[PDB]
Image (cartoon, rainbow over all chains, first blue to last red):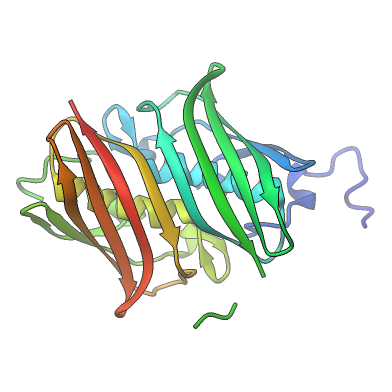
Length: 137
Length: 121
């Protein structure tokens, strides 16, 4: 498909298959995706703070998580696990770019590496495992 | 939240309700809202990790603390208004650095587990 994807002015999200219900205002702005990668950008808001000068880990990891899902961009996918390092505390007004790249893939699962950068300095790094298929036992 | 030394600025409606804390343990309860969804039947990982993170910080309960790393397994997708209790317990501490284990359960079925490393300055 699809005519809507062609079009000078097609929204970037048009071809995005994952997290259809996600409000980017609560997570991160999608910047690009495709070819086994994605970038999102988090500009933290006051509601995201844990402390006056520390953005809550849920929002830092939440942005990384979204980048990771966008790199694979598959309909029926879930994050199953992650190992992540929050290298420095982030304040509001800091723009953090999260760049995801798939490192391993199969029909059933992938591993995606995410690096977060502030002014091109790494401040986050993580590996996410994603499962692609919901039934459970 | 008297005696609570961590996350003074955190909006509990956007995260999880603090149920109890003290003695190197804490429980919080996540009530998923629609704004938290990634997909119709999957709460975004950021809110699940956010809830666990809050639990972990309240277990240690130290001023000037920061989550420096985590290893977590999301064991099942979480859906709207499944109440999820996250129970955090310190497993290692040298004051400067601590490890907190957090388990989240829906009913008594385990939907989340992880280890959180916390630095205090």
